[PDB]
Image 1 (cartoon, rainbow over the protein chains, first blue to last red):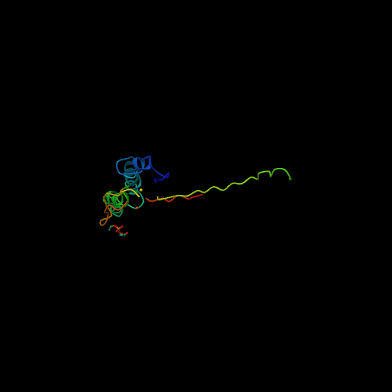
Image 2: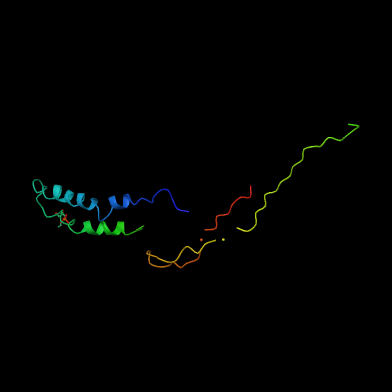
Length: 65
Length: 49
Ligand SMILES: CCOP(=O)(O)OC[C@H](O)CO
């Protein structure tokens, strides 16, 4: 038989690549990384401009329904 | 008694199951890568009771 835990495709369309999660995680870096030049003012927080698309691909393509 | 023997209740019954148907479913696818393939487981057996 089937299962009762899924069968609605609700969490897949909400927490996925083609949803709204990828938009709320791309603006959080510029909200704090682009304003920390007051006290620090050093080239340090620049290694996060490429790991955003990588972390979302190594976690969503694990199962894939 | 000494004229006619009264009947007594009696029952049996049997629930037999043949083949199974298982279915296938598965187918395939795967993714993762590888593987797946387708075978048917799926068989799914049934109880005879
Ligand atoms: C050089 C790129 O930035 P980081 O690797 O964060 O530098 C480590 C030290 O804080 C240098 O001051």
